Image (tube, rainbow, N blue to C red; front, side, top):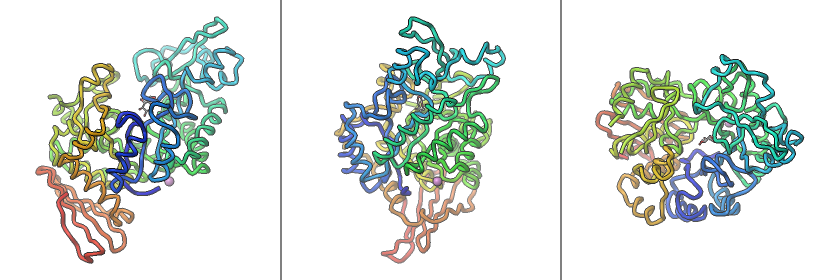
Length: 470
Ligand SMILES: [Li+]
C-alpha cells in the first residue's frame, strides 16, 4: 500500500456519479492523492450506504462497478465492510422473514429472546447509541412476533457472530470486493458485533479481537488491508496496531483544535512520541468528532477549554450519555475559517506517522451548510454538502485550497517520509517534526501562536537543502 495522501469522498456527493469524481480526480489531485476511500455505493435504506442490502452490488445512480475498477487501477481503493449489520430489505433478512424461524439466514441474525430475561442491571450495562433499547420486534410473514437485536437504525439489522454464517457472509463480501481490486477495507463498527448479557456488548475482550483477526486473515489472503474503526479510548486503537489492522487517528483532530486554539504544543508532542503505528490519520471526516477519542490524550481541563472556546458558522454538539458526546462542524469552520491555521493543521497531519487522509469538504475548504442539514434533519450533514463540478473548479481556485494542494502533492511525492520519523525538541508553543529517508530529508516547523508553517527539504536535483513556506 502506497504512502500518499488519500481521499475520503462520496460516490454521489461530488459530481452526478463516480465517473464524475474520476474526471475531477484526474483533472486535479492526480499528483496530490494516491488513494481513495469511497463511502459506500451499494443500495442502502439508511446511513448513506452504511446499511446496504448487499455489498455484492453498486447502486446504479452512483455509478457502475467498472468505474470503481478504473479508480482501483489508477489509485488505491478503500471501501466499507459493514461487518456489524446488514439491511432488513437485504434478501438474507427477507428470506429469514419469509421462512420465519426456519431460515439459514435467521441463525445468522441475532435474536434477543435467546438471552432469557435480562436484568435491569444487565440492561443498563449495555453500551447505548440512542436512548431506546437496541431491540427490534419483527413482523414475520408467519404472522408471528419475534425479536432481533440491532444497534443503529431499525432498517440496519445486527448479525451476531456466533453463527459462522456471519463470518461466511463476510468472506463472500470480502471476496467480491478484493476481486474488484479494493486495496483496503474499513471494518465499520466492529466493537458492537460482540454481544453478551452482563457485558457492555461493545469491544468485549478478547472475542472482538478474535473476530477482527479472522476477517483480517481472509482479507490478507484476499490482499485487501483492514482498517477497523472504533470510537473509544485510544488504547483500543493501539490494540488494532498490535493486530496489524490499521488504527485510526481519531485523537489528532481535537488535539490539534486545542493546540491551535491555545497555541500549546505539549500534548500534541507527547502523543507524537507515543502514537500508534500503522495509523491512518484524519482531520476532517464524514462523521463528527466523537470526544472520547481524545480523552487521556488531552486532559479534561483542556477538553473543557476546547469545548467552551468552541461555543460561539461553528460547531453544533449533540450528547446522549455525556455533557458533550460529539460536535459536528466542517474543520475549516472549526478553525474559524482561518486558513493559515488550517494549513498548519494539514501540515502537522501529514508529518504525523501514518497515511494521511483528506476529506472532500476539507479539500475544497468548504464551510458547513445548515440548509442541507435542516432538510435532512441530520446533524453530520453540515459536513456532507453536495458539490457541482463548476463549484469544484471555482473552489480549487481559492488560495487556501491551492496551498493545501501544493502541500498534499509534496507529502506524497517526497522520499523522506518512506524513511523514519524523528520528532525534534521545541518549545510549548511550536512543534518540529522531521522525516529522514536515506539522503532525502524534510522538516515541518509550525509556530502555533502565529500559525506559520515552514518546511525545509533536501532535493536531489538541487543536491542542496531548500526552505519553503507551505
Ligand atoms: Li500491516
